[PDB]
Amino acid sequence: TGGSVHSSPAIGQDGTIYVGSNDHYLYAINPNGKLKWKFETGGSVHSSPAIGQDGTIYVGSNDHYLYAINPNGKLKWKF
Image 1: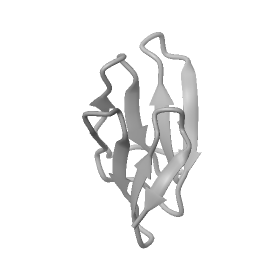
Image 2 (image 1 turned 30 degrees about the vertical axis):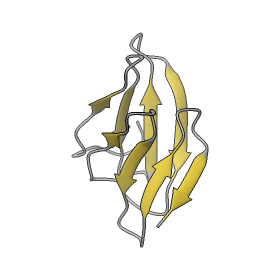
Image 3 (image 1 turned 45 degrees about the vertical axis):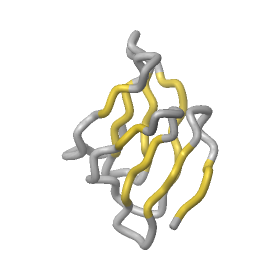
Image 4 (image 1 turned 60 degrees about the vertical axis):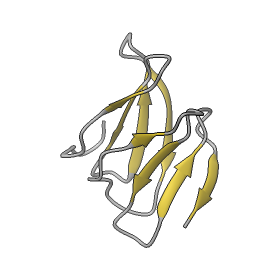
């Protein structure tokens, strides 16, 4: 990742690994180590992500907002 990470990873049901980064992204990494996608948030993601029953990924951000991201990496909403 760019920068660093004190965010703890979370695992999806398909084995995707999600982790935030100091460079402002939430990363979705495949179990083979290859990037699936990275979602651009407004600030450093030290929050650990949580995964909903439908696969939605939730993470907090140093800016305003809890983010809800679809498994395809597209914003569902920000609070």
